[PDB]
Length: 370
Image (cartoon, rainbow, N blue to C red; front, side, top):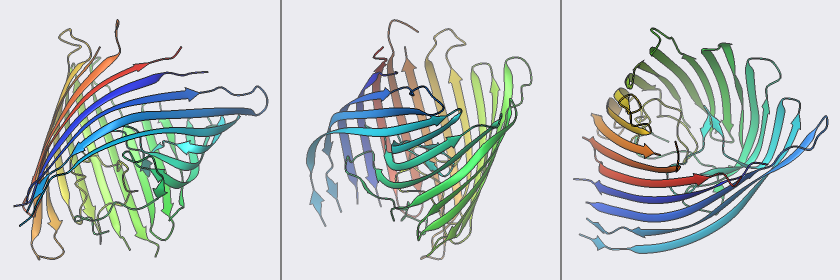
């Protein structure tokens, strides 16, 4: 019988350019109540989860080419999202509302309310050191709608891109610090995706280690995309510092395949770009500082620069390059609060079109209802 709600305050801001400028702003407040019941005793247990959403946004976005627009909007929404559970020993079946965290579908949650899916999920961990998941998702409610729509594919830009997204896979814990995953996905009439992963931590000296996250994926056509994505991030942790170098390469006839609105499982997927256009090679430098060291717990800094190049432009026979810079500072209050505040800053530039400056301020307070 777990509960708890979350209050969320979300200012957002996005200056979007072409040589044709657009300028969007959003103010928003949201309530997330979540209920996670228990199971009826027995060889099989019955349970039910509830997800309650409530909130109001406020959008402005004027734009210029000739042409000149100005537009304001206000929304309020509310939702209940039930998900029924069945347990057998150490295995689980949820039917109804889902928010999966897997290599082939990762629900997005960076805005007012979570992207959710309707479908079914079977998690089974009966063999010690091996989690398997199986499921199919039929519909999605995006993070800015409370009306479900059909699953689609992240298209457009330079990526070069039903009611049935099946998936199956799992992760074996070879040691207490050597994971290896494999996942499959299939979106009806769209793509079949394979996804191999390996994470390996390696402690060097008491208070410093080196994390290696090496990923490979392959999408193929069903009715067309054609893609391989190899990508790895290496993060050397030292005290309150973390230094991360990341490489990511797209190959094949189109960019990376994932369900529209999700967060692709890519190392260089960052604030504004996914750095996953056709043929795009990307590089990431990242630095993290945890102010726990200095004696100021819950304050963190992050900065990363990415550079992608070799982008097939399909049309104009040349190639595109783009680069991005993200800087985030985050305070999360240890008593007598759980008040979080996060500022996210994104600067993105290319040589083939877009140019985006983005800022996100977030204030979040979450409280266990018991």
